[PDB]
Image 1 (cartoon, rainbow, N blue to C red):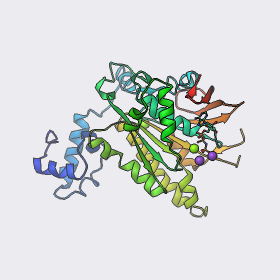
Image 2 (cartoon, rainbow, N blue to C red):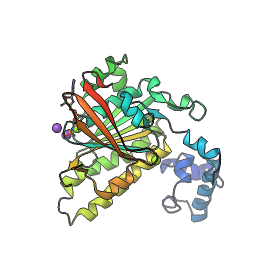
Image 3 (tube, rainbow, N blue to C red):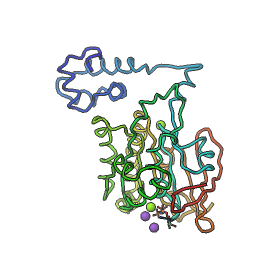
Length: 313
Ligand SMILES: Nc1ncnc2c1ncn2[C@@H]1O[C@H](COP(=O)(O)OP(=O)(O)NP(=O)(O)O)[C@@H](O)[C@H]1O
Ligand SMILES: [K+]
Ligand SMILES: [K+]
Ligand SMILES: [Mg+2]
Ligand SMILES: [Mg+2]
């Protein structure tokens, strides 16, 4: 931390206690939140930010560099051949991909299946030139359980059918039961602490994402307040995926209001989610994921199934 211009081991011991220990946390901070710290002046704060953006090389980039930045984004397999395809390879890190859909369409299954596929190194697709082996070594997931539907059994079950060891997944997956939007938001904010303690968090799950905000901000004369609180949440979730190069998955419910339906969460959720899906039930265990929004990929459908082994085909 003293590598930073104008940073005595004091101002450093201070920054660590205030949470800022990473050059990025500091490079992407504001001169206001940084001065909120004691002996940290304005020029002191202004200087270490400029210095960290610098050390981290956050300037203008052109040509081949645009490709090298893009190559830093690894991807997680959904165990579905078709879903990965439609996903442009798999679930991307540095982005928030959402799965919305009717009850029992498999949203939760996808969240569990992921926590498992993370513990299998051959399910993390990356370019060894931009993503080192150590950067994805001993990955860990973080399952923020909103509905109260996390199921250890299911994690164990999906683990064997894939050769993986069940306890091994449970030992590397942190679960946080949130009973309201408050606990929900705060848990997501406290993922930074899990990292500061050496946990290679490479997967974040919010299931469900909107349930809480709706039960709380009922009156739609309160919806302004909601969309506001809900916008900072999505912001935190994205900075996370960006800064810790991990994938952020979230599930969402569908509103009756008119395809036919639409994911709840309002505008803010739409703008904030990078990849948006609509999952449907088919005959028996046949399911369909429909990609309707993304920045570079074309809308498309993926067929898979939900069996005792999890997601397959
Ligand atoms: N062990 C299992 N073997 C086979 N199928 C299973 C198993 N466990 C769950 N399922 C299937 O998973 C389906 C439900 O998927 P699930 O992801 O839990 O719903 P959801 O998408 O989260 N819907 P919702 O709760 O409304 O948000 C069930 O109805 C079962 O057919
Ligand atoms: K249900
Ligand atoms: K539910
Ligand atoms: Mg991003
Ligand atoms: Mg569910």
